[PDB]
Image (cartoon, helix red, strand yellow):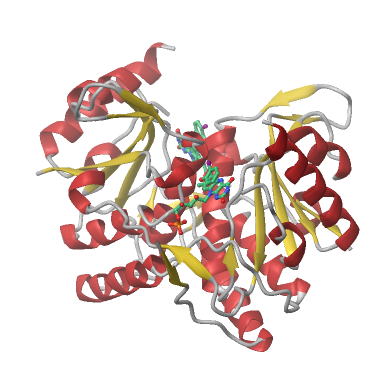
Amino acid sequence: AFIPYAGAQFEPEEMLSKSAEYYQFMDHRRTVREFSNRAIPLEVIENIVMTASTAPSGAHKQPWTFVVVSDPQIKAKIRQAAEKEEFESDWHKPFLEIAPYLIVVFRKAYDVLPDGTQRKNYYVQESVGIACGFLLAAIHQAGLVALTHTPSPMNFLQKILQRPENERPFLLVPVGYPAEGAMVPDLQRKDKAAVMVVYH
Amino acid sequence: AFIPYAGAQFEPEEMLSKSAEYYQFMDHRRTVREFSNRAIPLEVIENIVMTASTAPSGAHKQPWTFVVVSDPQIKAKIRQAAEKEEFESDWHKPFLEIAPYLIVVFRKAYDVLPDGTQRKNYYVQESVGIACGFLLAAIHQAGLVALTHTPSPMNFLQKILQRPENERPFLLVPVGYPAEGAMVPDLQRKDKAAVMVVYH
Ligand SMILES: Cc1cc2nc3c(=O)[nH]c(=O)nc-3n(C[C@H](O)[C@H](O)[C@H](O)COP(=O)(O)O)c2cc1C
Ligand SMILES: Cc1cc2nc3c(=O)[nH]c(=O)nc-3n(C[C@H](O)[C@H](O)[C@H](O)COP(=O)(O)O)c2cc1C
Ligand SMILES: Oc1ccccc1I
Ligand SMILES: Oc1ccccc1I
């Protein structure tokens, strides 16, 4: 069954101002590595996660699980293992505990029917990446900051968060208010000519 | 060098209302497959693409190229090849020509220094996926619709858009106004319990 698209549309003059304003808003987003431990309602994080989940996906499978962690002992154990692994191979990661939430994104390679059998999901890495994009935009929209982080150590995260075999950690995202006078590196984003090619 | 983070922050009551409102906005987004050929200023698409490019990336490499195509003969040739390939293995794809723009996202596996040598990029599939997420959010923000589409035929796209070896097509995104009375399938997104797990 099909239903008519319910979408607001605008004149070109309004799309110009909205697209320009949104670009400027998003350009202020920076990865932050120093957090305040100021409390945030769980309802804010739920809104953000379910926004990420509105992302398109291959064959509408939504092949993702978002694990939200605010429990301080699980955060401490994840920090310990993260630090240990990065040492062996800065490796100081207090943000894994100071941030009030960790969002751990898992990808689902297949689904398991209630009858044991498996069904492949489609374009999973792309789909889940897109959803992480929506996650980060929603975080920014809410007035929070985040640290996009490698999902490591991968096996430890899978075990302590008790996720099944059809899933694997994809990204790790501390979220919170920034620390007062948090600093970021003075980076410059690529200009239009270095990222964009236009045919006519 | 480092510089202080310049970010607006809000009280919990305001983050609640903003995160809730943004969720509702984003939940209206739907993949649309029937476009109007109403004209859109190139400046809108540029704003959208450069918004996508504000995405975080592994080691700040921004390992992506956005190819914007409005040229009707290139669009016709891409349509022809897309349709041909999907036939052999609906396969009617008029959107590839009716949409005023196609954005073709390429991922960069490595960079090529001006001196011939190569340097690996890091977490490319994740980084580019995130950027595609920002792309789609910016499209929605502007009041447009899009069709997130497999990058196929992969080789044809690489050739007709003349991209170098360190790059590969990642996603194909028609963008425009929706057709009047465009229809979407009557799908339901997963509920919180099917996508989200909370520890304390
Ligand atoms: C897939 C991915 C993985 C990342 N992993 C880490 C990480 O492990 N540690 C870290 O400090 N930053 C990590 N980052 C953040 C980048 O270093 C950061 O995005 C980049 O320096 C650009 O800064 P910006 O996001 O403020 O523009 C990651 C980013 C992405 C997209
Ligand atoms: C990685 C990816 C690839 C997709 N490829 C196609 C495609 O090739 N053809 C198509 O008609 N839709 C494609 N889609 C769109 C999905 O079918 C659509 O997102 C899904 O049915 C959910 O609909 P919604 O985005 O309106 O929520 C793709 C989506 C993603 C994320
Ligand atoms: O999501 C999709 C819809 C139609 C054909 C392929 C995919 I993946
Ligand atoms: O982007 C990064 C920053 C620090 C360490 C690894 C990555 I990938």
